Image 1 (spheres, chains in turn brown, yellow):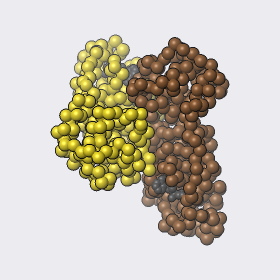
Image 2 (cartoon, protein in one colour):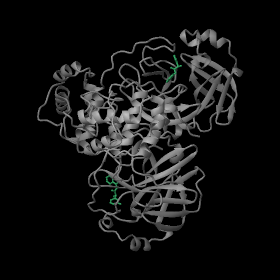
Image 3 (spheres, rainbow over the protein chains, first blue to last red):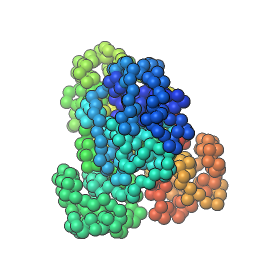
Image 4 (cartoon, rainbow over the protein chains, first blue to last red):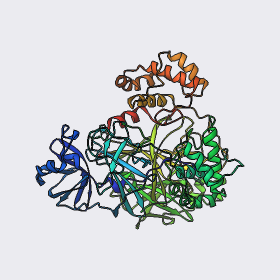
Length: 306
Length: 306
Ligand SMILES: C[C@@H](C(=O)Nc1cncc2ccccc12)c1cccc(F)c1
Ligand SMILES: C[C@@H](C(=O)Nc1cncc2ccccc12)c1cccc(F)c1
């Protein structure tokens, strides 16, 4: 038993991180087959970032202006192109350690592991969620750009996030691996507004089921509720409204615990209206929304990866 | 900026995990050079665990009773010995993926990463601390035995923990890699008492410094205090007493923030006596003690590993 914020094992991703240098700028790249993917703002100086014209900046660059280093192996660039906000550097050597992989654009509320890197080398790994306002609450310093977020399914690494920037508010923004930003953000040093950050209700419920599986049952009450009545309370506290798709996803946790989803919503409503009163749930004094229903099943059943 | 419970990258450890089978029991082993290390209770049945005589059980076993599998590679056992609570299986093939490594016995309050494994295959990675009562609050299911805890320093993997058992209270107990249990526990299915679990005060302080580095300054007050006066308050709340060694360790964080250690203790005292009053610190409604002062410097300076 027990419950932890668990990340995926990172070994398959560690072998894909390289260092990309263009002029004075050095950031991280992802080396899959014979292509390196990195943030396009590697071609900017500190002054260019206030208002970059990426097309005009990229035209003054040739293949030999990019230095790609994988530890002590120097890859030679033989082709380069800009795809949205990502640079694609075609190199002469295909990565031998290339895993089975795919590129995926996740939806808000889904979770993934981040491998934080600096100078092409791994620093640490942690789990996080894409917020409903398309930001992540990460841990990143200058030079972490190009670090990637990923999931693992069976033997396949699904890359879903590449880190680009820290907003003046301290939260983090980035793109999918096709270079499309998550959210309305642009890769330019200007004040940018993220929306209201709401709580991922379906995740909170999956975590309450995890608490029950692990012996924490005090929040369970005798009341019940309806989907419409619950959503009226949830929206007052800036919780995401619950839909029937969410009830279907929670089904397996309902079956394993014998607690109906709407009964769990009733318990949640009282926690919203009356607080936690100095008690804790799974060691936390706050309601936690960084576990999806799949995360809970995974951890509580012991799913492994090849 | 930002602050996350960050684990070490696990790639160097993933290549060392193997599956060990003896009769009907299968658990995880750690394969370094030509030796496999695993919990000695792999030689027990479900009935033997109530009162095992490990010497008598091990005598009825020969080299060919142990099946060691690394994915699809079958290692052949050519020697076996029992060292305290760990079995050492000498195999015919030295692990090619053996990293630079060492065995270390950590002290309570230090932190490490756990690679949770099942059937020799990685499942997830998370960070945790050795509690002052020598338990860990992990996330482990049946079959996770033999999963290891580790740190990384430069290029060297320091193995410090091997998982053996879940106590009837739901917390976890294990050994160093020489097979000596942390704490007073024995590898036998019997009711066992862990001591009082106290809060690691030096870790709480390092985390308050992390909060200040990250812009959370509301808990800072104008008061100050003395080491003796603080420890009198700390011991009332089951906090570990602070020593001069702890003040020396916190020095670099004091220098970077310009806040004297004793001034930080004063802030902590008021948080202990008056609570947090519904506010949060680094996203938490509880005081967090799973970050050492080194963890904080690491994350806030961007230390990488080769
Ligand atoms: C320079 C870069 C950026 O924000 N990098 C960073 C990423 N993560 C964390 C950081 C922490 C401190 C300083 C910089 C950090 C950037 C700026 C503007 C637009 C853009 F696309 C990229
Ligand atoms: C059987 C084994 C043990 O506790 N294994 C486990 C380790 N971790 C988590 C678990 C979760 C559920 C069930 C078993 C778990 C053991 C028992 C007694 C003494 C001993 F040395 C080992």
